Every structure is written in C-alpha cells, then in structure tokens.
Image (cartoon, rainbow over all chains, first blue to last red; front, side, top):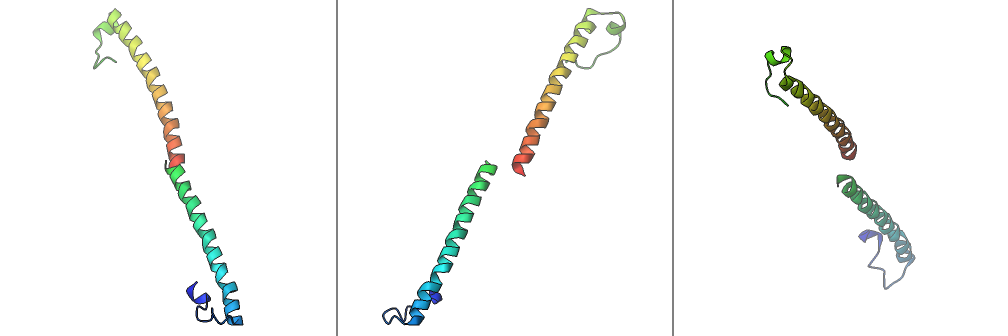
Length: 50
Length: 50
C-alpha cells in the first residue's frame, strides 16, 4: 500500500502520481474482500462450535 | 433389577422369582431405549464436531 502511492508527488500531480493513485486502490479492495471472508468463516466456526 | 440371584426359588416356582424376572425385562427394555437415544445423540455430536 504505502509505496504504491507517491506522497512525494501529491502536490506536483505527475503521471507518476496519477499512475500511483490508480495502482494503490486495488490492494485496499483485495484486502477488504479477504477481511470479509474471515469475518464470515469466523461466525461459521461460531455456529458449528456452538 | 435384582442383585446377585440363585436357584431355589427359581425351580420351586416362587412368586418372588416370577416378579423378579418381570422386573428385569422391563429394565432391559428401558436400557435399549437409552442406548438408541445415546447412539443417535452421539451420532449428532460427531457430525456437529466434524
């Protein structure tokens, strides 16, 4: 995440900066989708356990 | 059920024998129900654990 976003060029607004803003978002979305998969499997263990 | 029985009354056709053999067949009829309930209940446990 951190190094898929050029903080350095955020006032400058280069194609570098524009490439980064588009590239960083896919790992947040990946991650969000994996977090949900564990929250549901966790309740899955909570129901069969119980 | 009776605890530790021997032959005299049994062969002299005693009413004590006769009520004592009545009461153990019923304990064995109870026993079998308790077994098939324990079987199905431990089957559901094993399925719930798996």
